[PDB]
Length: 256
Length: 256
Ligand SMILES: [Zn+2]
Image (cartoon, rainbow over all chains, first blue to last red; front, side, top):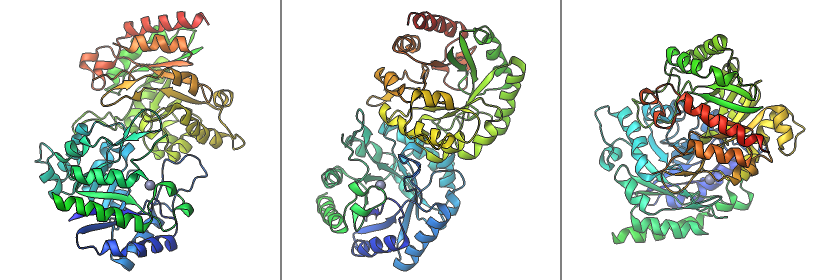
């Protein structure tokens, strides 16, 4: 099944998490999807000291665990520091390595020592071919015999790569669709349709393009009321918009 | 005085640190320079699990302290996690925020709570205008009354910005010299002549350009025998090469 990772950018409140979890129930039950509910417990890189951070590790994981129990959802969250991985893996089925930390050896190893699927975001600064080395760090942590990263070995060992765009001058990200093909030599590839759009509405067009190229899954942030969101309101889809997008992805994938 | 930050990329051994420290003694006594000896205790983002990492925090700081004591040098090192800052500041006169972590709030705040000068490396993915927000996080930590970052206030409070190039397609960094002017509105500006050169030596040429534009200091890594170095051998200058470069920088700066 194609992977769908969806949810709000940040944990805002348990009430908010519940509302979005509720509106994702139709997609979560879609037989053609392997679904994971996403929410960050920490936004580590915001513009100001006053910017909303999220609830942090302990309280965030507690809230994600509540969603897992109440909705039966598998969970994705991102980690930022040493010693978060093992604690987060008790709740999270996928642990995500942030794009800025995508080469960070200790974090990749620490996450790979857990039982979680590892989703490695490609840095905006990276050549897709060089992501093989991050995949290999993870794979060697799980099986020291592995010498070279391949899709099949990565799929078996739960290590994925995630496309989220590349720096294109200042304040602009471009999605090099060739990267989806290049990276898929080394690991299953997820396309992040939310964070990849920056320009100095394009989420569906890029996700359709990505589906046509060949991807193993979609990452897209969604919120019931984006204009009242505490992070990424301008770029999140409403649940009905996401359903439409997923419908199109599936139709495209059904051709090939 | 113009700042000079120089030393090996990584701490290789005490013997190596002493050898390069010895060769830097003439530069360190140049009264036109405010000199800091640099060496990383950890290389966090290397290609493979087997790549040389460095001695780690505890042993690294011991070695840097020995250099400070034996040579009288002020010290710069980079920190990678918040919990390292308070102990690192006991030895390092400057704590450097790595380029990939240049927006990381907790790290900037923790480092800024120490008495160290803060050297914030501009990420390869950043618009130089946006570096004001990282400077402001640091400044507000040191003086809550500050509303917007300026060169004067950053200088007073020991917060600097460091140019190290920008992503230019794949496997290429370009130095946008306009950035030196733009960032200097917000803080003193150091130019990193070592890590800014990547192409699919240009260090002296880019350093001369930077000197002509207007900078508060130079960061350049140097090693006695680069071909036998454990990190960044290809990009480090021999001490005599660094001396020539600094001589040229000072001649240019004396014109204006
Ligand atoms: Zn987001």
